[PDB]
């Protein structure tokens, strides 16, 4: 086994920019409910994940299949890491323009996460678990959350 080293505040892994092919790849444009690409999004109702849903719209649950798969893997690892604690999503798909101009939040490929107990001291390790869970980019963006994203299925050729 390898020793698990938490990410430090503002560290990102892999250590390259988010929207490079070695990480989560390109911005593909905003997804709105009326978009054809809204069909890229699937609602995550994993009982072992808490969703903040501050907008009261269920947007936080709507994400791409790859995002869902990586998040679901991480959910198991979080419960393993801290028995009694669960993975929590505080911001998923954003319909409201609350990020920078070309955010993967706008297309359901990024989630901001915490632990269910909101113990900020756990977040560096949470970030390392997100890397181990296979998220394509993980960024300890604020003391209050870890930003995790995935690539799209649209660079296969
Ligand atoms: Zn984020």
Image (cartoon, rainbow, N blue to C red):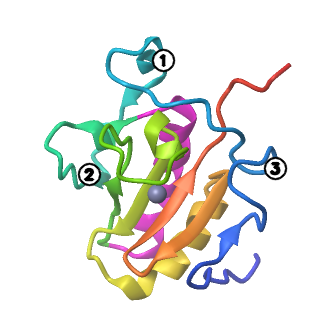
**Is-magenta flag for residue 69?**
yes
Q: Which residue is mark 2?
A: 51
**Is-magenta flag for residue 67?**
yes
In three-dimensional space, the C-alpha distance between marks 2 and 1, rounded to whole angstroms, equals 23 Å
Residue at the image point whose x is 28% and y is 77% from the top:
118
Q: Residues within 10 Å of mark 3 (few under 14, many from 20)?
A: some
**Residue at disc 2, CB closer than 8 Å to ligand 1:** no
Q: Which one is in front, 38 or 44? A: 38
Contact between labelled residues 1 and 2, with CB atoms less than 8 Å apart = no
In three-dimensional space, the C-alpha distance between marks 2 and 3, rounded to whole angstroms, equals 28 Å
Tag on residue 37?
A: 1
Q: Is residue 131 above or below residue 35?
A: below
**Residue at disc 1, CB closer than 8 Å to ligand 1:** no
At which x and y percent is residue 115? Answer: 35, 70
Q: Which comes before the other along the chain, label 3 or label 1? A: 3
Residue closest to the far bottom? 121
**Magenta span: helix, strand or loop, mainly?**
helix
Q: Which comes before the other along the chain, label 2 or label 3? A: 3
Q: Which residues are magenta?
A: 63-83
Looking at the image, can residue 75 be seen?
A: no
In which quadrant of the rendered image does the C terminus lie? top right
Residue closest to the far top? 36
**Mark 3 residue element:** loop
Q: Which of the two marks, 2 or 3, is nearer to us in this view?
A: 3
In which quadrant of the rendered image does the N terminus lie? bottom right
At which x and y percent is residue 76? Answer: 46, 56
Q: Which residue is mark 3?
A: 22
Residue closest to the far left? 56
């Amino acid at each position: 086994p390898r020793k698990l080293v938490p990410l430090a505040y503002k560290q990102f892994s892999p250590n390259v920019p988010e929207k490079t092919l070695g990480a989560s790849g390109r911005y593909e444009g905003k997804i709105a409910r009326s978009s054809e690409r809204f069909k890229e999004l699937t609602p995550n109702y994993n009982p072992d994940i808490i969703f903040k849903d501050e907008e009261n719209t269920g947007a936080d649950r709507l994400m791409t299949q790859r995002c869902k798969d990586r998040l679901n893997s991480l959910a198991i690892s979080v419960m393993n890491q801290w028995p009694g604690v669960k993975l929590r999503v505080t911001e998923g798909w954003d319909e409201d323009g609350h990020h920078s101009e070309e955010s993967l939040h706008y297309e359901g490929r990024a989630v901001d996460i915490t632990t269910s107990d909101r113990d900020r001291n756990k977040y560096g390790l949470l970030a390392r678990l997100a890397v181990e869970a296979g998220f394509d980019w993980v960024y300890y963006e604020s003391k209050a959350h870890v930003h995790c994203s995935v690539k799209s299925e649209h660079s296969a050729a």
